[PDB]
Amino acid sequence: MAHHHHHHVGTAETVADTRRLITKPQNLNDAYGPPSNFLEIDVSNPQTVGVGRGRFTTYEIRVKTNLPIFKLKESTVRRRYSDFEWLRSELERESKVVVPPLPGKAFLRQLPFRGDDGIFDDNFIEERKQGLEQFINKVAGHPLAQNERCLHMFLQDEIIDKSYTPSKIRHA
């Protein structure tokens, strides 16, 4: 039914034998360029989406690339700082990714408050934005990171799924 090893699609010439062939991990392939590729990500376009007690601001992650991992080459998602955090540590969990420290403990004791912490203020937001996009362009552009499934959820699909598969971008 769904799983079938018999096929006569199109012009049938070869039959459903085994012969040899085999399907083994042949490492990374070639398509656009080396695993470095060209890469340009921008976290920005904030949305303060949350509750009066616990309101958070989401960031839109914009990316253009010809990376063989990124799949869509160039797309945009939107998720919150808390997802960046777990993305950071996830890359540090089982890989030696160049993951840098998150932007914080800086502008907070630098700016006013007003919006509880000041997160409702458009100055602070971009102050975290600038560093968060700095952060991401590394963790989302480094060999080890392109090798961690964490990037698949961050740059691709729609959102970071906190129940995803803890493995590499390349799957068997």
Image (spheres, rainbow, N blue to C red):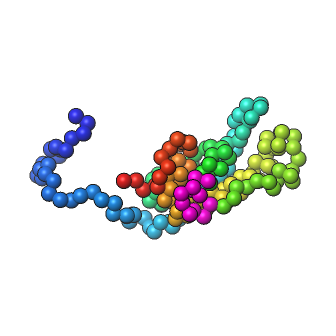
Residue 32 visible in rendering? yes
On screen, 143 above or below 51? Answer: below
Which percent across, then down, holds residue 157?
Answer: 50, 44
Q: Residue furthest front?
A: 94
Query: Which residue is depicted at the point 65% across and 50% down?
Result: 85
Q: Residue at x 66, y 56 (%)?
A: 133
Q: Which residues are magenta?
A: 89-99
Q: What residue is at 57 percent from the left and 55 percent from the top?
A: 93
Total marks drawn? 0
**Residue 8 in the figure: left or right of residue 169:** left
Percent of width and height locating residue 139:
59, 59
Residue 66 falls inside the magenta stretch:
no
**Name of the residue lying farthest toward the top:** 52
Looking at the picture, how far across and down is residue 160, in whole percent?
56, 44
Q: Quadrant of residue 5?
A: top left
- Whether the magenta-drawn stretch holds residue 95 is answered as yes
Give residue 87's position: percent from left, percent from top.
Answer: 60, 51
Of residues 39 and 93, the one nearer the viewer is 93
Residue 137 sits above or below residue 72 on the image: below
Name the quarter where the N terminus is drawn: top left
